[PDB]
Amino acid sequence: MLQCYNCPNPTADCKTAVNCSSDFDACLITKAGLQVYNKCWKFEHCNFNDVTTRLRENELTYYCCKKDLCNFNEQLEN
């Protein structure tokens, strides 16, 4: 399985590791101001439009990856 940081709410430093279900193929980290999101996700939705409409944030940067626990803060210069 792919293990990602996955917090249901934005969290300054998400430490919750979960085994994503096979529905997902990516780990996502997104920074929107001081809000940081960490999710099991899909690469088909790892794009600005799809992340903004799903997380309901106007302005953000994002990174997706497919190695264990790869969706960490330092991946995103922001």
Image (spheres, rainbow, N blue to C red):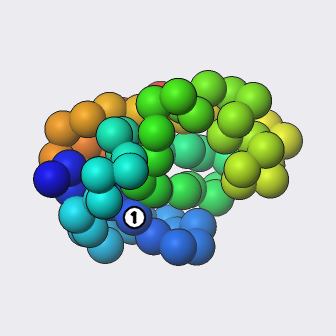
Find residue 1 and report its horizontal and vertical position in percent: 15, 53
Find residue 13 and report its horizontal and vertical position in percent: 41, 65
Q: Quadrant of residue 16?
A: bottom left
Find residue 68 and report its horizontal and vertical position in percent: 17, 47
48 lies left or right of 57: left
- Label 1 belongs to which residue? 6
In the depicted view, which residue is nearer to us: 72 or 18? 18
Name the residue located 34 percent from the left edge and 40 percent from the top edge. Answer: 25
Find residue 24 and report its horizontal and vertical position in percent: 38, 47
Name the residue located 45 percent from the left edge and 70 percent from the top edge. Answer: 7
SS at mark 1 in the image: loop
> Looking at the image, can residue 73 be seen?
no
62 lies left or right of 67: right
> Looking at the image, can residue 32 be seen?
yes
**9 w.r.t. 38: above or below:** below
33 lies left or right of 74: right
**47 w.r.t. 5: above or below:** above
Looking at the rendering, in which quadrant would you find the C terminus?
top right
In the depicted view, which residue is nearer to us: 49 or 59? 49
In the depicted view, which residue is nearer to us: 14 or 41? 41
Residue type, numbered disc 1: Asn
Name the residue located 45 percent from the left edge and 30 percent from the top edge. Answer: 43
